[PDB]
Image (cartoon, coloured by chain):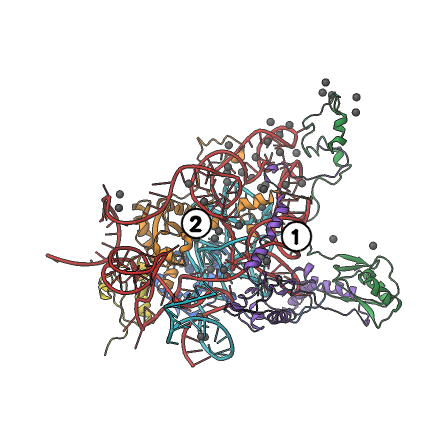
Chain colours: A blue, B orange, C yellow, D purple, E green, F red, G cyan
Amino acid sequence: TVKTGIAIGLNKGKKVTSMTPAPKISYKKGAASNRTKFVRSLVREIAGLSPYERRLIDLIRNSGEKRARKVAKKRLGSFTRAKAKVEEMNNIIAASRRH
Amino acid sequence: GAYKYLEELQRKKQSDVLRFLQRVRVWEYRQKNVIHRAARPTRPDKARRLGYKAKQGFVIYRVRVRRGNRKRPVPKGATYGKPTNQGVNELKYQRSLRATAEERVGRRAANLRVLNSYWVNQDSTYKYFEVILVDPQHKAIRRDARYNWICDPVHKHREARGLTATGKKSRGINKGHKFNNTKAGRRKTWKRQNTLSLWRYRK
Amino acid sequence: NDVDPIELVVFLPALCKKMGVPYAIVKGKARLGTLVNQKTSAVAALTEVRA
Amino acid sequence: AISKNLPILKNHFRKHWQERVKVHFDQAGKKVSRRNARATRAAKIAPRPLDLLRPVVRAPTVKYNRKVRAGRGFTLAEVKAAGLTAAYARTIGIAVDHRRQNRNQEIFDANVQRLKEYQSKIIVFPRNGKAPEAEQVLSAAATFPIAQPATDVEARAVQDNGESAFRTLRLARSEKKFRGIREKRAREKAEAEA
Amino acid sequence: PSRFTKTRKHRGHVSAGKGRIGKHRKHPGGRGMAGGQHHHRINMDKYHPGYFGKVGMRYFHKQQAHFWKPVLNLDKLWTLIPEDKRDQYLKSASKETAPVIDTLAAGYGKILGKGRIPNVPVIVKARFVSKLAEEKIRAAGGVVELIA
RNA sequence: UUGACCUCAAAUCAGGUAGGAGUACCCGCUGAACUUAAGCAUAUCAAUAAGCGGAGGAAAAGAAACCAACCGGGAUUGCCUUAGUAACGGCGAGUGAAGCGGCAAAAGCUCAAAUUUGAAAUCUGGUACCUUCGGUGCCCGAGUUGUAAUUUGGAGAGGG
RNA sequence: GUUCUUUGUAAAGUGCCUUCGAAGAGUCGAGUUGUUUGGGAAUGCAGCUCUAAGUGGGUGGUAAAUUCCAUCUAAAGCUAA
Ligand SMILES: [Mg+2]
Ligand SMILES: [Mg+2]
Ligand SMILES: [Mg+2]
Ligand SMILES: [Mg+2]
Ligand SMILES: [Mg+2]
Ligand SMILES: [Mg+2]
Ligand SMILES: [Mg+2]
Ligand SMILES: [Mg+2]
Ligand SMILES: [Mg+2]
Ligand SMILES: [Mg+2]
Ligand SMILES: [Mg+2]
Ligand SMILES: [Mg+2]
Ligand SMILES: [Mg+2]
Ligand SMILES: [Mg+2]
Ligand SMILES: [Mg+2]
Ligand SMILES: [Mg+2]
Ligand SMILES: [Mg+2]
Ligand SMILES: [Mg+2]
Ligand SMILES: [Mg+2]
Ligand SMILES: [Mg+2]
Ligand SMILES: [Mg+2]
Ligand SMILES: [Mg+2]
Ligand SMILES: [Mg+2]
Ligand SMILES: [Mg+2]
Ligand SMILES: [Mg+2]
Ligand SMILES: [Mg+2]
Ligand SMILES: [Mg+2]
Ligand SMILES: [Mg+2]
Ligand SMILES: [Mg+2]
Ligand SMILES: [Mg+2]
Ligand SMILES: [Mg+2]
Ligand SMILES: [Mg+2]
Ligand SMILES: [Mg+2]
Ligand SMILES: [Mg+2]
Ligand SMILES: [Mg+2]
Ligand SMILES: [Mg+2]
Ligand SMILES: [Mg+2]
Ligand SMILES: [Mg+2]
Ligand SMILES: [Mg+2]
Ligand SMILES: [Mg+2]
Ligand SMILES: [Mg+2]
Ligand SMILES: [Mg+2]
Ligand SMILES: [Mg+2]
Ligand SMILES: [Mg+2]
Ligand SMILES: [Mg+2]
């Protein structure tokens, strides 16, 4: 970004007139789109939950968002995707209780 | 496009609906001959995705394979050698079951050309594949500019050489540090870096 | 009511009910074929219609 | 075995090395081949010049960014900004690279300039077979050298200011090295209420 | 050439030049570096102390010349100025028209302070300088310009 | 009662195709031991021999889920380098690449996912005819459980 | 270099305007076993078990939680030297 012209340190680099190049479509690869949003929501209505998902929600409304998050992390494999399931399943629980 | 609903339904293999289809179809597939001609893709969106078109000269076969490790086919377990190679029972084939499935229908319909293939079902004993073959003698293909590449002599049995999809995977061929051995071709990069190069004026 | 693979068509009652479209699951895979001059047809649906 | 006071060699020849020995007897032979195929490519490629026009590009690593180097293709932005289409520039003698961006106007400008200078210096025969003939110039890279920039003058004025160059680097480094600790100690303070 | 070779002068004496008792045999003591820790230990510390065991840190995927900082001593420095153009500034020392020396351009990456430079101002630009290099450039009316 | 459809067959039905050989080089599978370690089992030999399957005049690779950490580079392949280096190893014997740099050659791209929906616009075959590596007309069949056009992320689509 | 031809009112390129912008799943990924690699809390492959997502996902040569950053866009395909 703002180089300093010096060979070393907390933003080392040779100074140059910047030039921010146009964005690539690629860099928007996992990008939403209202079509897929419609399709995925619809497909989920028709299909329902998976048994572990069904297990997951029973673990959210019990124990906690922690206890259940570990279970998810173990099942999907990766702590990040776990939380991601829980948040997604929490939104399903919203759309149940306060229908 | 109904296809977009197919793809996303197909992601839901533990939905009550798909589980039901899974149980009924795998039974059906088990009763038919290990290799049989499929009348049509079980997954028309998937075949679609992998190069299949609904014209004449596109053929779908279905095939069972036996699932598991490769038991070292040796006399009575006998290895006769160093204790490293003394294993029999935990050894795994370096090709995918899918690679086996392709190669076997590809042997049966040897007039066709294996384009690609895809999983469809499995039990404990078996995995099931649908294999997209393509007639290269059928003028519908020969005249189709998008597909006459496979008419070439240079593609005879691409599955047998690991040129299909499953092949270039097992064969470990992608760019980057992770594929230093295997990507220029395993044995080839080897032979290279194991060659003495001798110039006329020695360097 | 007889499409195979059935997943080509299962989502249509749901697709409709959501789009506020009147649908009907009719008996006749190839009867809807006779309808539009083919051997079979999965679907058939008029949108225009004369007054 | 091991003996005398000699370096400890590591000559890897325990492997049937003899089976894979490549001696280049055809060094002479394949040079002639390499030429009898450049002339014969120049022949059929009419008055065209055997190589594409290739960009200027900085070249990477702390080791090499001092020098500047002929890149691959010309980026989309440099081709448009030189006033022609991607699809068309290729049909001439211009290499175009869809990947590779522009973040350095001094290179980018130097490249659009590079492009224009080229356009003026060719002639693009119309589709039919009547022609000014024109001799076929074989290179292009030799026709359009990539030379290194200016950076500074052969001499000029001396300008001190007590600030030690050494001290700066030292201090530049110390800064980097403690940055995170420093933040944490303040981030710690950034949790001291009542 | 063979005709120049001891094994021509040995023709006609039994046993080449290799003794009658001790023979010339296939690998007594073993092939290569066998038993550096055993029957060849003496030679392998003496002539080669240090050989066995580890020391220091590993470094995965070390990329040579991340560390590319070639050194230039004041010792030379004035070599980076063309022979002819050199005496020009040399006789006309001045803070007015002092020769700018781009050492990065010349392939270096750090000025080290070995030697003596004459009392003639210089604009020295480089990544990295020894503390003394700077102190000697400043001594003779020059400066260091940190570049990249 | 007659006519479809789906699936599954049969025929010396109509036209085709596969096999076997070679195998120096090439794409995969499978796979040793001798030998080295002065013994030996991990290791080495070697991801080698032998065995198996499949190609071509080249094969494979290939237009990045790359390299990088720069002022960034830009499909693949190969040579000179990197380098007997980083690393691996009874850290023993022994093994051992990658990025950048110079060069040879250079070349780029197309599908899937989109309503043609005011018109399946696409195709095999048959038959006639002709100026026959094919053309047109006609008939059957394929095909909407999707054949063309269009678009392939560098984008691009629909309206002004 | 001729010469028939048959293409055309059909194909393509570029400027701004706006709304959009579909992008491959028993895959990616995780556990584990085996094998291989210079790849070392695991280099590729492969068996079984688990199995995703869409400001997602992959990489970033020391495991993990957290915060950023950089770079590409996988699971379909062709291609001369
Ligand atoms: Mg054995
Ligand atoms: Mg062993
Ligand atoms: Mg072993
Ligand atoms: Mg394939
Ligand atoms: Mg390797
Ligand atoms: Mg060697
Ligand atoms: Mg040996
Ligand atoms: Mg030769
Ligand atoms: Mg060239
Ligand atoms: Mg003598
Ligand atoms: Mg004597
Ligand atoms: Mg005698
Ligand atoms: Mg004797
Ligand atoms: Mg004796
Ligand atoms: Mg040092
Ligand atoms: Mg000196
Ligand atoms: Mg029969
Ligand atoms: Mg017949
Ligand atoms: Mg054969
Ligand atoms: Mg073998
Ligand atoms: Mg031997
Ligand atoms: Mg031994
Ligand atoms: Mg011995
Ligand atoms: Mg022994
Ligand atoms: Mg081994
Ligand atoms: Mg062999
Ligand atoms: Mg041949
Ligand atoms: Mg060739
Ligand atoms: Mg090829
Ligand atoms: Mg691309
Ligand atoms: Mg490259
Ligand atoms: Mg090992
Ligand atoms: Mg020992
Ligand atoms: Mg060693
Ligand atoms: Mg090895
Ligand atoms: Mg081309
Ligand atoms: Mg537009
Ligand atoms: Mg237009
Ligand atoms: Mg267009
Ligand atoms: Mg993709
Ligand atoms: Mg093996
Ligand atoms: Mg491993
Ligand atoms: Mg992988
Ligand atoms: Mg980049
Ligand atoms: Mg290919």
Res E18 seen here? yes
Picture quarter with ligand 10: top right
Q: Quadrant of residue F157?
A: bottom left
Residue at mark 2: chain: B
Residue closer to the observer: F118 or G27: F118
Residue carrying label 1? E62
Residue B119 image position (x, y, % from top left): 39, 51
Chain ID for label 1?
E
**Amino acid identity at mark 2:** His
- Is B95 situated above or below D68? above
Say few, some or many: other residues with alpha carbon within 10 Å of mark 1 (under 14 / 14 to 19 / 20 or more): few
Label 1 – label 2 distance at C-alpha: 42 Å
Q: Which label is found at residue D4?
A: none
Q: Nearer the viewer, mark 1 or mark 2?
A: 2
Q: Which of E120 and G24 is in front in this view?
A: E120
Write the residue at 40% across / 52% down: B151
Query: Which part of the image, by quadrant, shows the C terminus of chain D?
Result: bottom right
Relative vertical location of residue E81 with respect to residue B24 in this rendering, above or below: below
Q: Where is residue F7 in the image (x, y as percent from the top left)?
A: 26, 52
Query: CB atoms at circles 1 and 2 under 8 Å apart?
Result: no
- Residue B155 is labelled as 2
